[PDB]
Length: 163
Image (cartoon, rainbow, N blue to C red; front, side, top):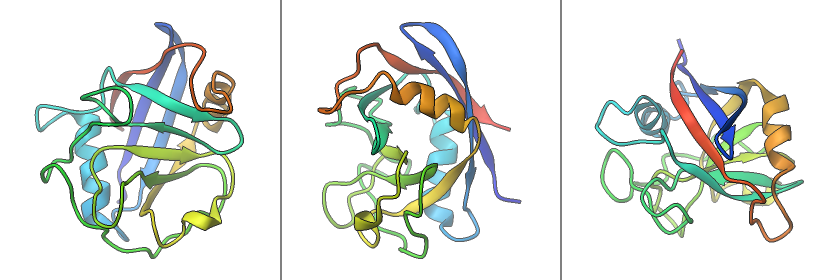
């Protein structure tokens, strides 16, 4: 019953592979729905064609800024921002999908895929999914990152949608 969405990842335009995510709509329905809808593009905007603009190996990959491509943009399907839905789920290890934000109740479209346990984020970022298939592809993406987060090649979501 929880939805599954996929990203097909490209590196400098060359296909890398597919990552799929389970979205925890049972626990965080509003947050899950935002990500789902941005992944299908059904509202007229979304993730297709957008980049990962900050990848720090041993920490996380961050994406979802489809308006400014650098961490300063994005918007949700509910408006510019929306509230922190709950903090039921924790950052338990690699593969966790969590919302980026700029303070309390400022969730937009940006998210990060953890590649480490990041327990210091618990109660401050809303966890709403996990990698289901293709964690190996996330690990491959991580190799293009750097300590300061700049990527050495352009990592894009070449296609995305619901499975």
